[PDB]
Amino acid sequence: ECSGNLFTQRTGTITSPDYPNPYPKSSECSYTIDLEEGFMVTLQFEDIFDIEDHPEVPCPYDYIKIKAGSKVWGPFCGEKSPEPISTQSHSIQILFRSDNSGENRGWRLSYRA
Ligand SMILES: [Ca+2]
């Protein structure tokens, strides 16, 4: 269980469950950053980024996705750390799902506004 996290603080670090040890099978995580209008969240991945991937199909197993307003970043997977995100928004949703197999360390991100 890791759905429904709500952050109202302007700074924080968020990780996949158990990071940097493998995230659970069948995860459905969600994290909402809810700030006052006018604030603009910036997000950066840090340290190891390791989400299961596929050599031909883009992120079919596990992935993190970020949504703000109408804008979507990702899904992201694999070993490459996504580039930093300047969301231009005060209300951000961070979603992570995993399937029922594999072993991967997950992700860590920090945010600021
Ligand atoms: Ca998996």
Image (cartoon, helix red, strand yellow):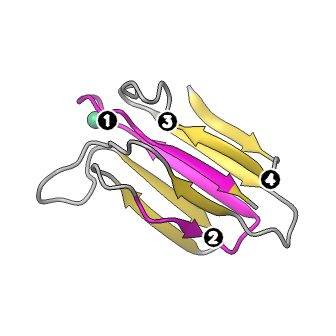
**Magenta region includes residue 100:** yes
Q: Residue at x 66, y 71 (%)?
A: 69
In the image: residue 26, left or right of residue 6:
left
Which one is earlier in the sequence, the residue at label 1 or at label 3?
3
Q: Residues within 10 Å of mark 3 (few under 14, many from 20)?
A: many
Q: 94 above or below 106?
A: below
Q: Residue at x 49, y 35 (%)?
A: 16
Callout 4 secondary element? loop
Which one is earlier in the sequence, the residue at label 1 or at label 4?
4
Instruction: Give the label, 2 or 4, closer to the camera.
Output: 4
Q: What residue would you read off at disc 3?
A: 16
Q: What residue would you read off at disc 2?
A: 87
Q: CA distance from mark 2 to mark 4?
A: 14 Å
Amino acid type for the residue under numbered disc 1 = Asp
Q: What residue would you read off at disc 4?
A: 10
Which one is earlier in the sequence, the residue at label 1 or at label 2?
2
Callout 1 secondary element? loop
Residue at the farthest front position? 47
Asked if disc 1 is less than 8 Å from ligand 1, the answer is: yes
Task: State ligand 1's quadrant.
Answer: top left
Which one is earlier in the sequence, the residue at label 3 or at label 4?
4
Instruction: Give the label, 1 or 2, closer to the camera.
Output: 2
Instruction: Determine whether label 1 and label 2 are within 8 Å by CB.
Output: no
Q: What residue would you read off at disc 1?
A: 99
In the image: residue 108, left or right of residue 25:
right
Asked whether 30 or 39 is in front, the reply is 39
Occupied quadrant, residue 43: bottom right
User: Quadrant location of the C terminus?
Assistant: bottom right
Residue 34 in picture, x, y percent from top left: 78, 54
Instruction: Determine whether label 2 and label 4 are within 8 Å by CB.
Output: no
Asked if disc 4 is less than 8 Å from ligand 1, the answer is: no
Which one is earlier in the sequence, the residue at label 2 or at label 3?
3
